[PDB]
Length: 311
Ligand SMILES: [Ca+2]
Image (tube, rainbow, N blue to C red; front, side, top):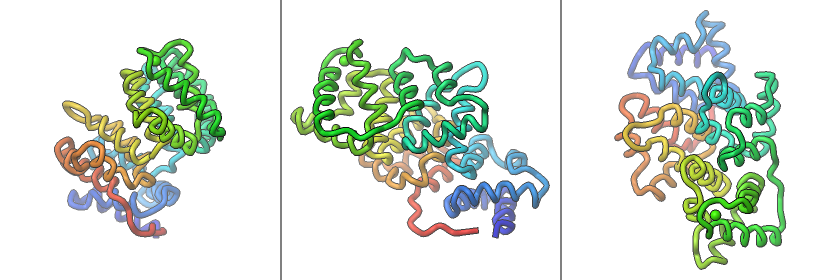
């Protein structure tokens, strides 16, 4: 069982033609079993998995594999820690993580974060990001708040308010609260309703297009990402992946975290990617990424269409 999977990992790193077995293993078993296998690797081989991978894999691919063999909640906490520990802040990482997880998952990681690091997740995020930028107000609200159901009347009121905000150039002082309340505190069901209500009321205008009008820079990415996550997580994954493939080269740290966080749940990513961007995901990946790393990203995002195996 586990001993067999360990030997498959060993062989994958010793024969270049078998490197993707590491990815097949990630796709074939639940995260808790992958973590068990990682723990068992050390016991069996006398070498820690990360030390072994380092000898055989490039940094991008090693980092990806390590992210895959972790339980989700652990991965999320480690990403937030990585983005905040020391001198700088990786603001993009904090946005990618906090805005694309369910409210129950935020609750779970607040507690796990404290257990791992003896720090408050909300407090570390606020200390590092401040609360001036709209993207910062948004992730702070998400980090410490809840998403609670609302009635149609409240949605009608907020609809008028968000339209007002969309119509004015720049985020006005009276508009800050509208944007944060909707994007940080709406449930998925209510946000989907509001999205459709906006199109219904404003002659087919788009709420996401209004986000684009209102915001720029990381604010714009953050509110688009929150929009897409609430509306359809598969669209959010496609959006984040498109941005990560962005421009001259590609953002491998971002590619890794978006892929590791979302590949298992967001099976429609490739479909929405083509629907929205016109180009097949695999074709963009082929252009942007060479070698085994590109093959791994393509494979992880290929929908698994069969039951998982067990160790
Ligand atoms: Ca405005």
